[PDB]
Amino acid sequence: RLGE
Amino acid sequence: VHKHTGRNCGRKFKIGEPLYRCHECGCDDTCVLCIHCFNPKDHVNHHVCTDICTEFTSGICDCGDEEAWNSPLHCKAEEQ
Ligand SMILES: [Zn+2]
Ligand SMILES: [Zn+2]
Ligand SMILES: [Zn+2]
């Protein structure tokens, strides 16, 4: 996943 | 080289690296694919957006993680  | 048969890809993105999202295929907005994994033949008439990993952004390619995708994927790195 991609986040932050 | 980028083959990950039998497991997830899990490549952690670096600053400036491109990534892929598909509106149809991703379970949510956070589901992403690296360039070595994204296969155009999986998303023929889908809505795909390319993004770039920034300083303010972090994470990993979900190719091979079935929880992340509404449809089975066919990894580009698998192709000869
Ligand atoms: Zn990948
Ligand atoms: Zn892959
Ligand atoms: Zn798709």
Image (cartoon, coloured by chain):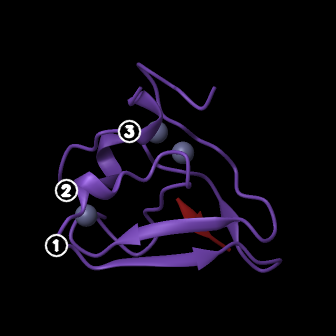
Chain colours: A red, B purple
Asked if ligand 2 lies within 8 A of label 3, the reply is yes
Q: In the rendered image, which quarter is residue B64 located in? A: top left
Badge 1: residue crowd in 10 Å (few <14, some 14–19, many ≥20): few
Q: Position of residue B41 (x, y in %)?
A: 25, 53
The disc labelled 1 sits on which kind of residue?
A: Asn
User: Would residue B27 be found to the left or right of residue B37 on screen?
Assistant: left
Q: Is residue B78 above or below residue B35?
A: above
**Which sits in the foreground, B28 or B35?**
B35
Q: Position of residue B18 (x, y in %)?
A: 63, 67
Badge 3: residue crowd in 10 Å (few <14, some 14–19, many ≥20): many
Badge 2: residue crowd in 10 Å (few <14, some 14–19, many ≥20): few
**Which sits in the foreground, B12 or B44?**
B44
Q: CA distance from mark 2 to mark 1?
A: 15 Å
> Any mark on residue B75, and which?
3
For the C terminus of chain A, give its image quadrant.
bottom right
Q: Is residue B20 above or below residue B55?
A: above
Q: Is residue A2 above or below residue B78?
A: below
User: Would residue B33 be found to the left or right of residue B53 on screen?
Assistant: left
- For image coordinates 77% across by 80% down, the residue present is B56
Q: CA distance from mark 3 to mark 1?
A: 18 Å
**Which sits in the foreground, B41 or B20?**
B41
Q: Does label 3 or label 1 sit earlier along the sequence? A: 1
> Any mark on residue B70, and which?
2
The residue identified by callout 1 is B45
Pointer 2 chain: B
Q: Are marks 3 and 2 in contact (CB under 8 Å)?
A: no
Give the residue furthest to the top. B6
User: Would residue A3 be found to the left or right of residue B57 on screen?
Assistant: left
The disc labelled 3 sits on which kind of residue?
A: Cys
